[PDB]
Image (cartoon, coloured by chain):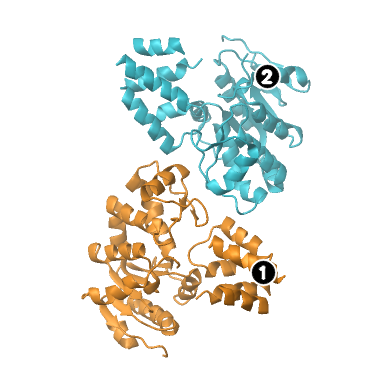
Chain colours: A cyan, B orange
């Protein structure tokens, strides 16, 4: 149910099914906490989908509290990486770089860290098992005292959804926030490229202090094929894909999409789009 | 004489020797033109040395006219590249780029452009004779209408001292600003590594619309070792270098300079200092 989780103020684990109630329970809990808390502290809402952040933000409405509603990748950049990169790693490192997921991939953290200073763009990890950005954000927090002070003094609770898609390294940063930075966590999981269901599924059994709640249902890549199909009938398409797409990257993507709008050329376009980031899905695209 | 220069409103050649009179006559002419002109137009004072910019800028004082006093590369980036890069070359190209002379050098213009789109950070040309940044600025002006409109409607006269030390690429842009965009020019030449004095000397007699005014004396790398010697006894001597210097590059300069403060170590740090950027000079350094 919804009443008892509203009363609870500690760490809350929600096991909503099919995502029907995830966004609804997120908005309700956020409003309840914001109206109850009269202090200067604010909340941060992080979503894998950029569109999911936008629809959530629209439901809270205008507010000057300073709350953060955005993507998981956009949270670390805006709140941890951008302001405190120079303090943690000296003035040489830049704070005006740009994150590009498709280009400039590296193989090792040390190589990824060493290219970062000279490249002046936020690089990405070629391997899908690890996320370099969240390792860098975690490293910044440990190194920088002011970064630790700011995070504690800014946020009192963090709202996370789609936690079963969270990477193991991404899980590592959040548990850093919860354990010594003493920040309440409201994470939602359901039974992303480097998705690690292991960390979320094992979290329920490993930790007993966390509170778990399972709401009733009523009260994998086919999504993006439907989105390009409806677009054929581009910025909205960007919100569906996880992360924040660069202008250069989306212009290249849009060039491929307008090339789509015969069956043979349809299949080749879907192949390269998948390469940039199933035999049944291509047939469905051919049908529509 | 000085009063002959002041009342002239056209294009002025100044041939002052040793730089004693050219520095004070540049400030005097700038003040005279600013006082005389009551319109919204401003002037741009560009110098090879960053130090020369501040010493000139300190002689005008605080003003809301919107005048520009700075380096040649600083003028091109702040007034042409940064605002109008996206308009000329599409939204894919960035404007949060940074200038780094020591790394990411380009061998070809088209390759230099194509690496710029993906690396997203400005750099210098590998060949010192060519300055990739300035033809990029010239290319931006030719392609962007708003960039051409802004420059014409902002500045009515440009002050470029040490024009005999100007490069061919820099000369190409300034002449485009003069004859094509109809902007008054005020240059100084007294007969940067990759430049040539031939262009200025040739332009003395090649151009008939230009005015040749002679300024008498009384009215190569010796400095760089003197600046570090007084530093031994970091942002100051870095400012004396030609062009804007990145913070990381300054830090690298700092870590290679502090090693100097035996004789053999002195010679080797001088050698790679030149490599990053004479037998008599190293001996003089050993003496001091």
> Does residue A61 appear anywhere in the picture?
yes
The numbered dot on residue B266 is 1
Q: Measured from the top left, where is residue A91 in percent x and y?
A: 61, 54
Circle 2 SS class: helix
> Does residue A43 appear anywhere in the picture?
no
Q: Measured from the top left, where is residue B174 in percent x and y?
A: 31, 65
Q: Chain of mark 2?
A: A
Q: Nearer the viewer, residue A234 or A23?
A: A234
Q: Which residue is mark 2?
A: A198
**Residue drawn at the location 50% of the way across and 57% of the way down:** B101
Q: Nearer the viewer, residue A189 or B77?
A: B77
Q: Measured from the top left, where is residue B95 in percent x and y?
A: 43, 49
Q: Nearer the viewer, residue A87 or B108?
A: B108
Direction from residue A142 to residue A218 in the image, left or right: left
Residue furthest to the right in view is A208
Direction from residue B225 to residue A279 in the image, left or right: left
The correct choice, above or below, for B122 with respect to B203 in the image is: above
User: Do marks 1 and 2 share a subunit?
Assistant: no
Residue furthest to the bottom in view is B218
**Residue drawn at the location 64% of the way across and 30% of the way down:** A170
Name which quarter of the figure residue A255 lies in.
Answer: top left
Which quadrant would the C terminus of chain B be assigned to in this image?
A: bottom right
Gap in angstroms between the C-alphas marked 1 and 2: 58 Å
The correct choice, above or below, for A158 with respect to B233 in the image is: above
Which quadrant would the N terminus of chain B be assigned to in this image?
A: bottom left
Q: Measured from the top left, where is residue B175 in percent x and y?
A: 28, 66
Circle 1 SS class: helix
Query: Which mark lies nearer to you, 1 or 2?
Result: 1
**Residue drawn at the location 46% of the way across and 77% of the way down:** B59
Q: Badge 2 local density, few (<14 within 10 Å), some, or many (20+)?
A: few
Name which quarter of the figure residue A200 lies in.
Answer: top right
């Amino acid at each position: 149910s919804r009443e008892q989780i509203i009363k609870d103020g500690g760490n809350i684990l929600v096991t909503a099914g099919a995502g029907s109630g995830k966004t609804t329970i997120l908005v309700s809990k956020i409003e309840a906490d914001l109206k109850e808390n009269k202090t200067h502290y604010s909340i941060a809402a992080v979503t894998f989908t950029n569109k999911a952040a936008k629809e959530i933000e629209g439901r809270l409405g205008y507010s000057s509290r300073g709350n953060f509603i955005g993507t998981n990748d956009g949270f670390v950049e805006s709140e941890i990486i951008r302001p405190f990169i120079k303090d943690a790693f000296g003035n040489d490192y830049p704070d005006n770089f740009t994150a590009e997921y498709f280009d400039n991939q590296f193989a090792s953290y040390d190589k990824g860290l060493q290219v970062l200073k000279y490249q002046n763009i936020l690089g990405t990890y070629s391997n899908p098992k690890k996320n370099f950005k969240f390792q860098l954000a975690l490293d910044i927090l440990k190194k920088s005292l002011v970064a630790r002070q700011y995070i504690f003094s800014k946020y009192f609770k963090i709202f996370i959804d789609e936690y079963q898609d969270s990477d193991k390294d991404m899980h590592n940063l959040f548990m850093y926030l919860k354990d010594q930075l003493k920040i309440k966590l409201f994470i939602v999981g359901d039974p992303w490229r480097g998705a690690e269901p292991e960390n979320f599924n094992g979290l329920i059994e490993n930790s007993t202090d966390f509170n778990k709640y399972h709401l009733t249902s009523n009260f994998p890549n086919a999504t993006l094929l439907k989105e390009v199909i409806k677009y054929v009938k581009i910025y909205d398409l960007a919100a569906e894909i996880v992360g924040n797409l660069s202008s250069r990257e989306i212009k290249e993507i849009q060039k491929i999409i307008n090339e789509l709008l015969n069956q043979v050329l349809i299949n080749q376009v879907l192949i390269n789009l998948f390469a940039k980031l199933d035999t049944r899905e291509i047939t469905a695209f051919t049908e529509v």
